[PDB]
Length: 162
Ligand SMILES: CN(Cc1cnc2nc(N)nc(N)c2n1)c1ccc(C(=O)N[C@@H](CCC(=O)O)C(=O)O)cc1
Image (cartoon, rainbow, N blue to C red; front, side):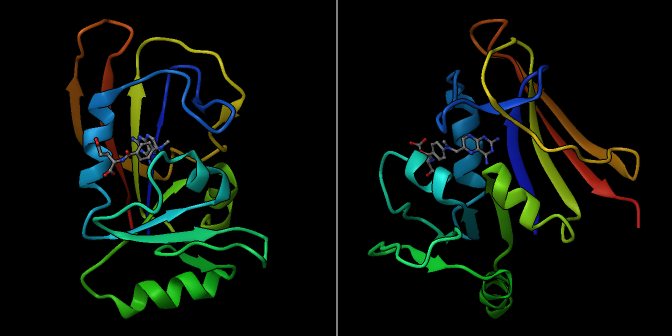
């Protein structure tokens, strides 16, 4: 279990399913935090991708529908199902990308929280759920600037105390 999402100083994490801004640098970190491991995306995030299914790593789609289809991607509709699939692979980890509906499902199972805090402000309707940052600690933090000042991003890594 590993949370992973990108937000700005306002807390927004997307807009109409697709992102409002464009941070190509963050896309390079997503490919490294997915290839080799198991990717977990919902239905709104699955269609948000341009090329589907996503190669280089396993695809795990979770929705409340029982009539979906995808040649190459895995279609599941049970929390225990996604857990049994992750337990079967000891050399893989469960990465939660989104959307917010999927994050609510894996709320009682998360120790590492990866998030990218930006600097420029943006407008949108998609926001991040209310999490508790008092029972966590930051051990890793790398600031990365981009060509513009509004496209600045900082990779933060929070972890549970015990
Ligand atoms: C909309 N979306 C979801 C998305 C976008 N930004 C994020 N940013 C962070 N920090 N974390 C996430 N989970 C995240 N998820 C996307 C958009 C593009 C690709 C994508 O093309 N990924 C390629 C990147 C390859 C390339 O750069 O060409 C990969 O192989 O993973 C994936 C998810």
